[PDB]
């Protein structure tokens, strides 16, 4: 499908790299995509994510469970048609009402349906996909918090109204926002997974490229869909190996050392960051088409996983070449 | 999912061993963790669940009974798949209704099928695991009390409205909250046998160790605890020093113990009753000039303080003369 | 034809678009679709003024006399309309300009106007970058593949209607 890999580009690598890594492991965290919205972030997301194997799931099912046996009682979807559908991407609007985000339970509907009274909130209809947050900065703190953990753990908690409504929510939180607004809640910023480094200059050509792929996709004459599909699968293949190596470490007396050294030297210490960096870096090799371990992997992910917090410096390369 | 290394957590020459003790036996008492928010109390609790071997239990089942033969009547287990799954740890947020805590019960659903009308509450999904508490200080009395006894006994008693609803709830209760609000309910200290905190080393020592085991993250369960094993002695000493003088100060057959026992041994929930008894008894003792509020005085005021909120039917004398 | 119910009925009428002179760079599509862009010449001098009073007061019944004296003026009015048509196809050349832009939307599964405005703007912006003084149909269709799609039921057609 119309995806824009690393075939030819010198700039927006961070964007792709981050969104791909999170697609592998959700434990990384929400991708804090810096930069303005004019860059057409959502546009890129609604193309890049197409590489992922079109998920198998019930037709109009919000959570889109594969088999009917995994459909939550409230989601009594009559059309139990298990079909193939592309990666769902929902653009989280700025200033969205928290209740509308997760869902609610109407009183009238409740007394006449019970659990069936649950409203299909945004996240409820964004499972197994991507959630593009416009701006994490100019937004309610509690909204960011909720979204961050939901994406982390994996449950769209709707314990409100009068029932403990809940259901899985495994999705990639694309937390977009401006470069910086004013040290807004560093605690939440740390919780984020990777972030597109703003300090590094980028090309402009990617703009036209993305726009063209946006056009040549919707109602594509069976051209761009096929062409890229093989590559889509190739990447997916490596993604499997990444997860296989996720709970393992090929070279202990290497990855652990270099990783910790970088974090400490840059002063960007923090269990949350460190342990995540060590994982993302290893999984990174999948996108590179390599084994797993590699110093430069740690270095690259460092200038992403650390970037979204204080105590960071360009010393990355200078610390450990 | 990626978890933080429980052993390697920054210091914590208290919380760690405390949680381990309760893992052997929950009867020891609830784990009361002092300290501020930065201590990361919840982190430790959940981190332990990671190292704890996946408990054997049915797939689609809240209480997660090992064998299908132990499934509660009211329950409706579909997937009777006995498999392995991580230790269940649920956080109890402040403000949650008692309904969602123990279990919900709809009236319309009741008349339809009272048996399958009882919805499994949060505690049901915490059986054979750990239940974390929010700000126990500000949390409702009836909530804290209920949680305490349930963890103590082992059964989530919901014998109300005639329906003798019940189900296993063998879990470890971890009481959280700020250091101290202002002369809070003493009963907490009594029932929370493991009143520890979270020692946070400012100096190096552990700091370096954390980074190393977080980055590389070794797989050897042995090496995961080896270096930390010695510290258990220090922690043990802390606990010993407390027990060494507890019975001396809070002498049995008097003090908080008996006060709480009286309420629990009678037809009533708890806590709120105990607080009333303690206050009145202390006030009376002051007039009597009795420095030590003996059981006699506790029972004396109980005949009034409890009666107007407790189903009196003798017992008191038979339990505590 | 909405909500499944294919409701329909004759509506053979003449549409008279009114409004103030100009608000500020309004939707150009109006000028295209409104083939008869005229006004209301208001004579300050006498001439008609006297005629009005006379035919308003007495108000004759003869349909012929009602138009007779006014028949000659149709020539002048006609000239006005002719002068426009004389150069319209020259400026707004067919197979390009507003015509095709509006046609694309109407020839597809969507209502209109709001779509056309989106197409025109994007196409013009692109043309500026291309340096193409005249926004050719090719560019119009190019942007249409995105501008319309997210608000129009795309099912080919475009090429078959306007290559």
Image (spheres, coloured by chain):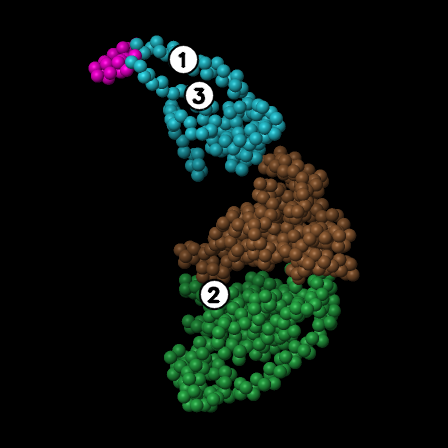
Chain colours: A brown, B green, C cyan
Task: Please determine if labels 2 and 1 lie on a single subunit.
Answer: no
- Numbered tag placed on residue A133 in the rendering: none
Task: Name the residue: 62% across, 80% down.
Answer: B239
Task: Name the residue: 43% across, 87% down.
Answer: B286
Q: Position of residue B261 (x, y in %)?
A: 49, 82
Q: Position of residue A104 (x, y in %)?
A: 47, 55
Q: CA distance from mark 1 to mark 3?
A: 14 Å
The residue that label 3 is drawn on is C35
The residue that label 1 is drawn on is C78
Disc 3 and disc 2 in contact, CB within 8 angstroms: no
In this view of the protein, can residue A24 be seen by the observer? no
Image quarter of the N terminus of chain A:
top right
Based on the displayed image, in which of its 4 quarters is residue C22 positioned? Answer: top left
For the stretch drawn in magenta, the main secondary structure is: helix
In the depicted structure, whether residue B71 falls above or below residue C53: below
> In terms of secondary structure, where does tag 3 sit?
loop
Residue stretch rendered in magenta on the structure: C47-68
Does the segment drawn in magenta span residue B229? no
Based on the displayed image, in which of its 4 quarters is residue B23 positioned? Answer: bottom right
Based on the displayed image, in which of its 4 quarters is residue B79 positioned? Answer: bottom right
Q: CA distance from mark 3 to mark 2?
A: 67 Å
In this view of the protein, can residue A189 be seen by the observer? yes
Task: Please determine if labels 3 and 2 lie on a single subunit.
Answer: no
Packing grade of label 3 (10 A; few <14, some 14-19, many >=20) is: few
Q: Position of residue A234 (x, y in %)?
A: 71, 45
Does the segment drawn in magenta span residue C67? yes
Chain of the residue that carries numbered disc 1 in the rendered image: C
Task: Name the residue: 53% across, 67% down.
Answer: B134
Q: Position of residue A244 (x, y in %)?
A: 71, 56
In the depicted structure, whether residue A268 falls above or below residue A198: below
The residue that label 2 is drawn on is B95
Q: CA distance from mark 2 to mark 1?
A: 80 Å
């Amino acid at each position: 499908r119309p995806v824009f890999p690393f075939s030819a580009i010198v700039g927006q690598e961070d964007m792709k790299l981050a969104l791909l890594l999170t697609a592998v492991d959700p434990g990384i965290g929400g991708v804090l995509v810096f930069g303005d919205r004019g860059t057409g972030k959502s546009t890129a997301v609604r193309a890049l994510a197409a590489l992922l194997p079109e998920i198998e799931a019930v037709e109009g099912c919000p959570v889109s469970s594969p088999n009917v046996e995994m459909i939550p009682d409230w989601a009594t979807v009559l059309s139990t048609n298990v079909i193939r559908k592309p990666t769902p991407v929902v653009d989280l609007p700025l200033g969205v009402s928290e209740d509308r985000v997760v869902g609610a339970l109407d009183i009238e509907r409740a007394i006449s349906k019970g659990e069936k009274a649950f409203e299909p909130g945004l996240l409820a209809r964004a499972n197994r996909g991507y959630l593009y947050i416009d701006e994490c900065n100019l937004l309610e703190d509690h909204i960011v918090d909720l979204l961050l953990d939901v994406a982390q753990s994996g449950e769209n908690v709707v314990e409100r109204d009068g029932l403990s409504i809940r259901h899985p929510a495994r999705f990639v939180l694309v937390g977009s926002g401006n470069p910086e607004e004013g040290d807004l809640r560093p605690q939440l910023l740390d919780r984020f997974g990777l972030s597109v480094e703003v300090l590094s200059p980028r090309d402009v050509e990617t703009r036209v490229e993305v726009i063209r792929r946006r056009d040549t996709y919707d109602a594509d004459p069976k051209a761009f869909l096929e062409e890229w599909r093989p590559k889509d699968m190739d990447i997916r293949n490596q993604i499997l190996e990444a997860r296989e190596r996720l709970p393992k470490v090929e070279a202990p007396n290497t990855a652990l050392y270099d990783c910790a050294a970088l974090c400490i030297a840059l002063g960007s210490d923090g269990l949350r960051g460190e342990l995540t960096l060590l994982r993302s870096a290893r999984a990174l090799a999948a996108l590179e088409g390599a084994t797993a371990v590699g110093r430069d992997h740690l270095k690259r992910v460092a200038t992403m996983a650390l970037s979204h917090r204080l105590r960071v410096a360009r010393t990355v390369e200078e610390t450990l070449p």
